[PDB]
Image (cartoon, coloured by chain):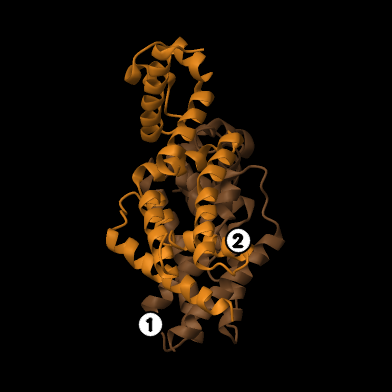
Chain colours: A orange, B brown
Amino acid sequence: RLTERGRQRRRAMLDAATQAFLEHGFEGTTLDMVIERAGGSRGTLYSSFGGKEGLFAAVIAHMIGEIFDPAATLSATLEHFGRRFLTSLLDPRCQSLYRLVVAESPRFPAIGKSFYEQGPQQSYLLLSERLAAVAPHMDEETLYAVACQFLEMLKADLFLKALSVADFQPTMALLETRLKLSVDIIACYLEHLSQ
Amino acid sequence: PRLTERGRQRRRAMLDAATQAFLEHGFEGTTLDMVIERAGGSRGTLYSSFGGKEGLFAAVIAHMIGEIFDDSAPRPAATLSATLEHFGRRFLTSLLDPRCQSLYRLVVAESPRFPAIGKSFYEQGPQQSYLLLSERLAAVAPHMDEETLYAVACQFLEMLKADLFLKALSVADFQPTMALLETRLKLSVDIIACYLEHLSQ
């Protein structure tokens, strides 16, 4: 229902709403705050997004693209993917995206389901495909299971700690310590798996 | 803050009602009036016992930590695989309990507003689980570096969550089957045991 000028106003409102939700969470973010940051009118927002839920759904989907959407050896494949995964995950905006979805998934189940499929699940599937290239004779179901365990292992004593402990900031030294161990563990397993 | 027995009963009763209320409605959707309706008493006694909504919520979180983790409530197993499997199974059964999922949702949602609550949760919950396993691991791997054992303990417990815990937190229809739990547990045990059995050469 929007012209080119309408598409500009919509993208502007989406950017302001994104910033607002990150700072204040869903409950503390009002449509008035979005109008004050992005200009325009409260009514034009209802037409573009449908209301607070529709706006919040668009904000989550927009952030998913922002944060989410070949090496010679297995160790380098794990290391390169693991590093990019940790840098994306530990970004404070990504932490907020996770906090928002976990807080509001019961109230908005469609948003939580969309987040998982297009975020974490896509990360698992992408690694599984890269792993198949360097381990071409391995069961695809096993590679997917291993891919999930590797990516989750990178979060250990880091992601939930950052989400729960306000002063705690993961150092780059911490990331590299966890990355090296996780790669060593998973590579060891795969290098002994095929007998 | 109450020296009487009847005050201690009313306080524990209000704590139980508030716990159920916060679990169902979250922090923002839980009012002190809802707690009074479930636990009886008066709004004023709630303010005296807990200090207000923040103090009540802090007590609720701390209470839930004891309920779900409950100190050291197993026996040392003979093998490394059994040690990982037994601890991993108890960890997953505790973690995937719908009340535990709610405790995690509450803490992550409210940690920025109440940093003291989030920090207390981590130290007394997940961090204690990591430390307990690392101690059990030292018994069956007595010549291993304790810093490495703690690092391995953390990785094992977190990998048990893979494609499971966050999925349950985010996907409303998704319910982890016990078949799924056992599938993840067997793989994680196999991975970590393989690593440790080659670490000391």
Q: Of marks 1 and 2, which one's residue comes earlier in the chain?
A: 2
Q: Chain of mark 2?
A: B
Q: Nearer the viewer, residue B81 or B93?
A: B81
Q: Residue A46's x, y, as percent?
A: 50, 15
Report the side of A170 relative to B153 (left or right). left
Identity, as a three-letter code, of the amino acid under mark 1: Asp
Check chain identity for marks 1 and 2: say if they share one.
yes
Q: Residues within 10 Å of mark 1 (few under 14, many from 20)?
A: few
Does the image show residue B49?
no
> Marks 1 and 2, how far apart in space?
28 Å
Specify whether A159 is left or right of B169: left
Q: Does dot 1 land on a helix, a strand or a loop?
A: loop
The residue depicted at 28 percent of the width and 59 percent of the height is A172
Please indicate whether residue B181 sits to the left or right of residue A13 in the image.
right
- Residue A6 seen by the camera: yes
Badge 2 marks a residue whose secondary structure is: helix
Q: Residue at x 51, y 13 (%)?
A: A47
Count neighbours of disc 2 (C-alpha within 10 A) and say few if under 14, some if 14 to 19, many if 20 or more.
Answer: some
Please report, as a chain letter, where disc 1 is located: B
Q: Residue at x 34, y 67 (%)?
A: A177
Q: Which residue is mark 1?
A: B145
Query: Would you place residue A35 above or below residue A185 in this image?
Result: above
Question: Residue A180's spot in the image, x, y percent?
Answer: 37, 69
Residue at horizontal 55 percent and vertical 65 percent from the top:
A146
The residue beneath circle 2 is B94
Q: Position of residue B66 (x, y in %)?
A: 53, 59
Which residue type does callout 2 highlight? Ser
In the rendered view, tell whether residue B86 sits above or below residue A63: below
Up-down relation of residue A65 to residue B185 (above or below): above
